[PDB]
Image (tube, rainbow over the protein chains, first blue to last red):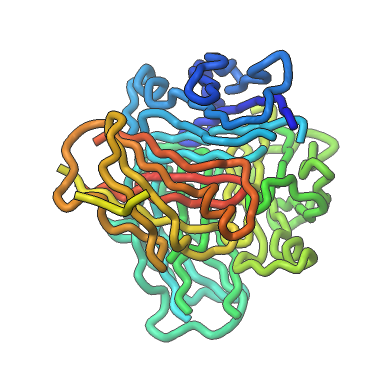
Length: 105
Length: 103
Length: 105
Length: 109
C-alpha cells in the first residue's frame, strides 16, 4: 500500500507547540523533503501524492532547535525509522531537552 | 509485594530530588515520602503490601512551583492494582508526564 | 475560561482507542461522562467554556482493556490539571504496561 | 551480526510497555561517525550494563535498538523498524520504552 505523511512537534518541557523545527524525510538515504514546522508545530503533508511502499526516515532537528533558543540537549536530533506498505501516517515528536518520544497517531 | 519509584525530570534530563510522594489504599494513606538525590524512593512500606487497589501520588505541581516553574498539571496520580516487586517511575515535565511498570 | 478535548491512542497496538469512558470533574462534582469515538476522540467536555479551577479528567483504561480480554496493572488514568488559553487538549497515550499525557494542541 | 564490545560509560534498559515487562533479546548497537563500536543484546532484565570496556570519549554517538526485528520474531507487527537515539558526550543511562505503536527515550539515572 501507500500512505500520506504528517507530523506535529510539541515541546513538552514548556507545554507549547514547537515552531520552526526543521524536519526531513528520506528513503534509503535519499532526501525526499526538508520542511519546517509551523506556529502550531505542524507539517500537514510531506508529499502531493501518497508515499510508495518502502523504508522511511523522518528526522527532526531538535538539538539545533533547542540550541537556537539558548538551550542544551543531550539528544542531537530525533530520527523515526518506519515502514510504509492505512491511508495516512501521523507520526508526532514529543520533545524535551532530556528525552523524546513518538507514536503512531 | 514491595513498591518503589523513580522520578526523572525529562525537561532537564536529571533526577527529581525532593518530590513528595504519597501512597494510599482506598483513600487511606499508607506512606508519605520524599525522593532522594537520585530521584528515588526505594520502599514505601517496611512491611510487604497485601492485594488491593492502590494510589501513588507525586506532588509534581508543587515541586515545579518551588523551582518557580509553571505547569498545567497539578499532581501526578497513578492508580494500580496488586493482585512480586512493583517499580512505578514517573517521567515528569511542566507540559506532560508518564508512568510505566519498570524493573 | 477554556474548552477541553482529548484523544486516546492505544500505543500497544498503534490504533485509536474507541469506546473508552472519560469523565470530567471539579471538586468531586462531575461535569461530564463521555465515550471516545472511532478516532479515539472527545471533541468537547462542556457546552460552555470551563471556568478557572482545578479539574480531574479520568479515562477508564483498566475497564477498557478488561472488556477486550487484556490485563493491566493500571486501573484507570487520572489527569489532574488547572485552568488559570482558548483550549486544553489533553491526550492519553495508553498501553497495558504504561501511560502518558501531555498538553497538546 | 556478531556480538562485541571494547569520560562517560553508557548503559541501556529496554522495557516493553505494551506488556509491562523487560525486553529480553533485543540487539542494540553503538556507533560513532559511521563506525560501529559495539553490538550487544539485552539480558533477562532488559539491560545492557556497558557498551565499552573503558569509558567512552567525548563525541557524537548513535545507539540503535533493533525493535522491529524483536517484535517480528515474537509475531507482532509494528510500523517502527528500529529505534535510533542520537546523542552527545558522568554516566549515560539511555533507556528505550517500546511498544508496537510507539517508543520513547530519556536520560535516566
